[PDB]
Every structure is written in structure tokens, then in C-alpha cells.
Length: 566
Image 1 (cartoon, rainbow, N blue to C red):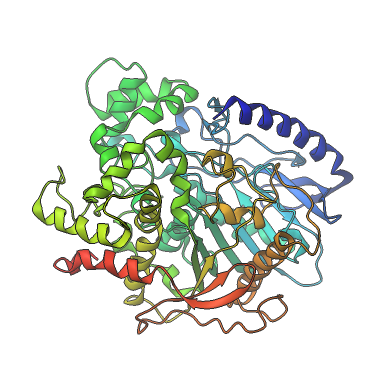
Image 2: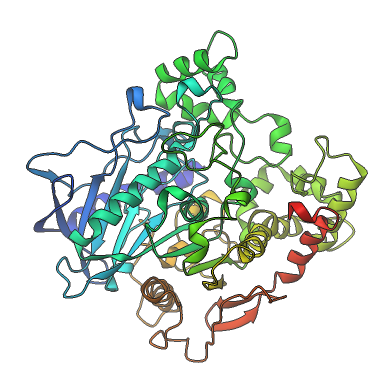
């Protein structure tokens, strides 16, 4: 990140500290939890609303020392009243702005918010799982403030979970009890805590909605796929991602050795010796070197992260992904709860900063060979069959005789988001009880109100609705400001939190109490549908056929002779 943004960020970080303090209130309160009493505090918002705030509630043992790389265990309960009036550290990670490692291994916490601790009626509970590619993210309110959602009568809960190698190391050797997916197992434990404790905060244990964006969407999908979480919640919302996105899972069993080697390990490639080194290394050294793990070949093959969700090599007590997510979709309990899914109108815009640093990437579109789904393509990506598959991609996104950055970014929207959604919808259709899935398309563009990922994607002064742009209208962040009540931005906040609350409440996202929705007839997708319909969210709310459907079908044509793999 530029020094410019580094200094601006530091200044906003100081401003956030002073605003957080001044928005603090003297009204502390105590709630029960199965692990003992917790003290929270009421806080204020820039819109003159208020909410009770409990942060730093442990849902697992701090995964330190011997617990490193291992499945979470339940935390030890306490006597007395545990202080939850301040946040805890985020998971160890590279700060996307400073470039330094921040965070702590002691990060397994969740935060609970509500405008009323004793509601006369039990409230819908919404659980947010943050994205960040499974390598960054937090539940701190400088990034995910509950300030907008608490104008609604819900309970909002924001969880953390282990990121990067600390969350997703996977070793083949069964003796070592590091099968993988530690971070997803953290999420499972957090959902169990929420199920058995939300009633203490005025929440309805029988009406829980899980939702997440990007890797948070993949995460929410995993929670809907795994047997571990069966019946733990009742609705799901997948925002710009799911578990069958190509970035959402990787076979990373061989990469632990590589990481150890980068971190100065001396010895052979065996799991036992590799683990014992990794167990003793400083957490910040491992996370720092994570960026170097992927081989040149892996990056060429579009493997995005060295460690992430994986198929576990053997089944243990807390095993979450015993098979590939595609196979898991076939018996998933989550196929049978009300579901909403969607993407922004220009997801691939997110890769602007990548293209600026590596403009050579645009040449990939001359054959589009590197973007053929890895399961279909040959290792070198020189097979004539992969050349013809890539040609189908190329016709769908390349506009002239030479490809452009915009063609590249448009391709990225499909490879990373729309095509996997299509594959999931069609897979899910032959294994479901008939519960509805609704689609939205987020198409509201503004620069009067933004979120920090715009800095990361170098998206300042760039037109279009990029991946992550919707977060601005769901959560307060430290770059936000109070918006006039009649502004297009403020209305989008009302509509987005309104639609999400309605869906969380009824399993149907439609409400006439939501301004703009008066002519909306929003039906679910059916298996018999050749063309998807979605609510397009812009200054106006409009039901339309998905504009992306044509390019989607073209991508699907790559599987003409390999229908079994679709």
C-alpha cells in the first residue's frame, strides 16, 4: 500500500479510537452464558441510535501452544463476571494496509449486538462470517460495525476464526491430528455457542441466519454443507461466493513442508518433523512467509491461496470436509433451508491492482488457457482440448482482436464468482427438498461512502460495482460518515439491511415496507428455469434476467464432453 494511504489510515485509526471512546456509554449490563456471566456496554452510532455491545466472548479455548493447528476445544468457564466491554485481537495476519503482521493466536472470539436486551418477543439472529480469502479479516467494529443493522429489531453476531496456515494447515500423517480445516472448525464451534446462548441476548434459537461475503460466503456455504452443523440454523445468505468457487478449497498437504522450509526448517520432508518445527516457530514468521509458498506453476494454474479449506485425508471427531464440496452438496442438510445468493455487477473490477502490477496477465486472454477449470485442463495447459476449452472462454470475454484489462476483469467475474454459483445451483437442484433460493445482483455504485477494501483493490476513482462494494451498506467502518437521510447511499443502507432482516425473519426477502420494492415480484429460482432471474439492486430495485447468463452458459459449454464433472 502507498505511504499516502498508510498515513491516512493511521490518522483514521486514531480518529476511530476517539470516536469509539466518545460513542461509549456508562450503561454496562450483564448477560448469562452457559460459560458464565458476561458484561457488555451500550454504545452509540453516528445516526443517534444505540445498541448493547458484548465483544470478546470466547467460543473456544485459545488455540495456542499444543492447540496450534488443532481443532478447537470448548473454553474453560469462569466464576464471576467476564469483561466483554472491549474487543479482542484479530487472527494473526498481514495487515493489508501496513504490510506488517498484526493480530494474535488468541483470537477465537465472537461479538453480540442488539438495540434491546429484553425484547418482548424473541428476535431473528443474524450471524456474520467475514471474508478475506481465509487469510485476513476480523470482527472489529472499525471494519464491521453493527451500527446499521441495529436500527432493526434483530440480534447481530460477528465471529472470528483462525486464518492462513494457523487456520488451515493440513498434514497427511494420521498420527499427528492435523487433518486440516481448523478455521472452519472454529466456525462450527461458534455456531454451537450461538445456538445455545443467543436466547440470553433476546435471540430466537429457532430462527438463526448465517451470512458472509467472499470467503465468508464460502464459509457460510461450508456450514450448510457439513454434517457437524445440522439444524444449527435456518436460513443462509451467500454473498459473492460459495464452497465450489475455485479459490474456496485447495489440496495443500504438500505445502506445510514448503512453509517450514521458508521459515528455516532443516531436515527432511516428513510430516512429523515438519509439524514439530511449525509448532515452535513464531506465529508472525509463518504468516509473513505465507505469501511465498505457492509455486510459479500453482499461481499460473490460478491457485489463489497456499492454505485454505481442504478435503481432510482422514476422518476425526470434528472432521468438517470429508469429501470434495461438490460431493458434499449431494446430501447437505443445508440444501433444505431457505437460501439467498448474489453477486455485484462487476466483481472482477477487484483485480485492478493486480493488473496494474502485472499487465502481462492480460495476455492470458489470447488463449484463455489458464482460466479453464483446473479439473478439465492438462498440467501444462498445452493440450489441444484445453486450447479449445480456452477458446470458448475467449469468445465470451474478449471483445476485439487483442484482449483488454476490462475483458480480463469481466472474465474474472465469471471464473471466480458467477460460474461457480451456476454450478452450485444446478448441482443443488438434484438434491433438495424444494426450499427456495433467491438471487440478487448488487448494482449500486457510489463513491460518497466507501469501505477499506477500496484501498486494497486500488479502487479509488474507479467506476463500477466491485467485489466487496456492498459491505459499505451493511456495516459501519472507520472510513464511513453520517449520510443525509434522503441520500441515495442512506436509502441503500435501509434497503440492504431491510432485505437481509426480512429474509432472516421469514425466509422470503420480499417486503412492501421496504421503499423501492413496491413493484417487485421476486420469485425463487426453479430447476426448470433455463434463465436465472434476480433482484437487481441499484438506485431502483428491479427484477431482471441475470445479464451474466449468456457468458455463464458459454462457460458451461466447456463441459460438453465431460458432463459428469459439471
